[PDB]
Image (cartoon, grey):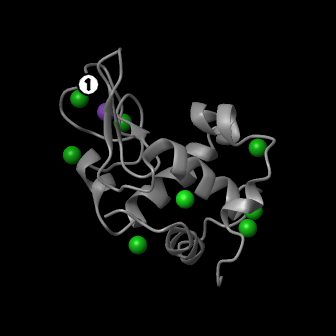
Amino acid sequence: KVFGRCELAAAMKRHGLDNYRGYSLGNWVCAAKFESNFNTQATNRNTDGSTDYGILQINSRWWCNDGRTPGSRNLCNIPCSALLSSDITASVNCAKKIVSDGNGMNAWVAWRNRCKGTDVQAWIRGCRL
Ligand SMILES: [Cl-]
Ligand SMILES: [Cl-]
Ligand SMILES: [Cl-]
Ligand SMILES: [Cl-]
Ligand SMILES: [Cl-]
Ligand SMILES: [Cl-]
Ligand SMILES: [Cl-]
Ligand SMILES: [Cl-]
Ligand code: NA
């Protein structure tokens, strides 16, 4: 599923992500934009052999099981395939664990490089929320 910008903002809000760990909704929408272009089915292999999954490109090295990332963990206790669903519940619940891990949203390198410090409210501007 390819979400619309305001559609995803509303789904993220419904699943409790707005201001989660102090990160406003626009931060989450901005991160999803540059991780996946709002496509729940996005996958991207990493040089280390892990794979990133879903709207927030959650990595198999630590967070989900895909059966092919040697020495990895599954700290969200989910198959990585669950992160590709049209229903964003699994991605949101796992992102809550990731953003609580110590470095906030810097865990998402693209958030640090393309969202951090910018006018992230632009990503929810005009949306009925
Ligand atoms: Cl957009
Ligand atoms: Cl917010
Ligand atoms: Cl915002
Ligand atoms: Cl594995
Ligand atoms: Cl584990
Ligand atoms: Cl599994
Ligand atoms: Cl959803
Ligand atoms: Cl923080
Ligand atoms: Na894993």
**Above or below, 30 relative to 74:** below
Q: Residue 40 location in percent, x, y?
A: 35, 56
**Above or below, 41 relative to 58:** below
**Foreground of the two, 60 or 26:** 26
Q: Is residue 79 found left or right of 18 in the rendered image?
A: left
Q: Is residue 90 visible?
A: yes
Q: Is residue 2 found left or right of 120 in the rendered image?
A: left
Q: Residue 70 location in percent, x, y?
A: 25, 19
Does label 1 point to a residue whose CB lies under 8 Å from ligand 4?
yes
Which quarter of the rendered picture does the C terminus lie within? bottom right
Name the residue located 67 percent from the left edge and 61 percent from the top edge.
123
Q: Is residue 23 visible?
A: no
Q: Residue 117 location in percent, x, y?
A: 81, 41
**Foreground of the two, 107 or 125:** 125
Task: Find ligand 8 in the image and state its quadrant.
Answer: top right
Residue placed furthest toward the top = 48
**Above or below, 45 relative to 29:** above
Name the residue located 47 percent from the left edge and 48 percent from the top edge.
56
Q: Secondary structure at mark 1?
A: loop
**Above or below, 128 relative to 84:** below
Name the residue located 74 percent from the left edge and 54 percent from the top edge.
120
Q: Is residue 17 found left or right of 88 in the rendered image?
A: right
Residue placed furthest toward the left = 67
Residue receiving disc 1: 69
- The kind of residue tagged 1 is Thr
Query: On the image, which quarter does residue 75 sit in?
Result: top left
